[PDB]
Length: 480
Ligand SMILES: [Ca+2]
Ligand SMILES: [Ca+2]
Image 1: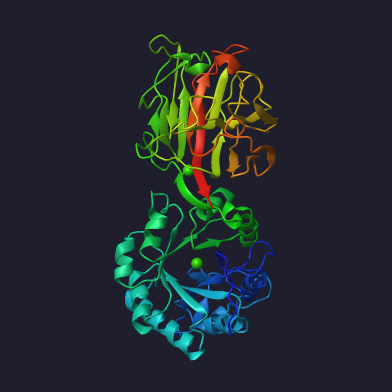
Image 2: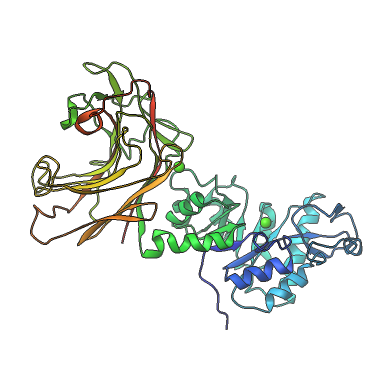
């Protein structure tokens, strides 16, 4: 019978923005149906004459909906000439198609909880009266309305909009999904916790690309959006569309020092193989700190043992290692001649031998004296920088210190692809000649900001660039 769409798009008040249709209007609902959204959401209020209407604000065109007769509301006209649609009108207009679900939100009553409970009862009756229980899914800010919907319809789709109640208690009261603002979900495992207990996850007021990508990365069930057309574009671009499934990720909502569950510290100031000038500190908030949703690796012009600079070098070794997959890191590079920020991966067990026999992968490398180039490199026993046989590529990146860029690798059995802003600039292939040409079976990611060195220091160190901060939005690793 029905041919439901399978996407995660939920049209917030319909697809009103792009075509300048009125919010919570028939044109907004029909535009969402035309786009192919999973569902269209709308807000219902009850007039003083107990006529259910569709509007978000409590006052429609200067008229309080709950305190005025429905006939008074018809004095007002929307931008496209529409009158405020009744719930029956909205339900009937959506009853004429079978591709897009109907997400119904009962706004909490500004009069009394009893009146709002009556609205909840009136909504269910009209849904049953028009025989559209298969179309309507329910979300609400009032928790009692959610429990009332479940009482009248035991298997109705119900979701909660306030983040106060725990996911475990929502399932206890037999709710079907959580629909919290996307800021609530920025707490380790919250999205995948609720999914573990069988609750669908929905996020609303999501109009920006980085948040949509973050939600799709953690595979949220639905995304309520005011930009449905933009979300569709990002759904095709997201790695989950290519089969990638997220195995490990740190979005850096930690707000403190790097999590001991995810990162270890490389400590020492003995050159680190490239005669580097910095001392990497151990659990020092002056060089590694998570604040405002981004990891901050900070190089400071400060003495540390026998070195004039201190910085940080965080390693995922012995905590998360992987073979193959997609690694995705979004970072804003620190500016200044003499810096050497790096996003790279080293083998955990070094099964083939010491460096460079077991290999090395450099997802992102940047030198401060050349601000137009970002380098991706692989290092092998046969191809490495010591003997000048390494294979790598540079790509000019615009505004690397002012805005975030996503540096990524796609690591397969046969090759490795290097990406900067979904553009593939380097492909390293397995030549099937053995470990010397291709030494890849399991590595671990590393994040560091080096000062000077045999590469970064060739032009000296502008000692005024300090303190220099590398900001990493997140580190995500997908696998097929
Ligand atoms: Ca709404
Ligand atoms: Ca973040």
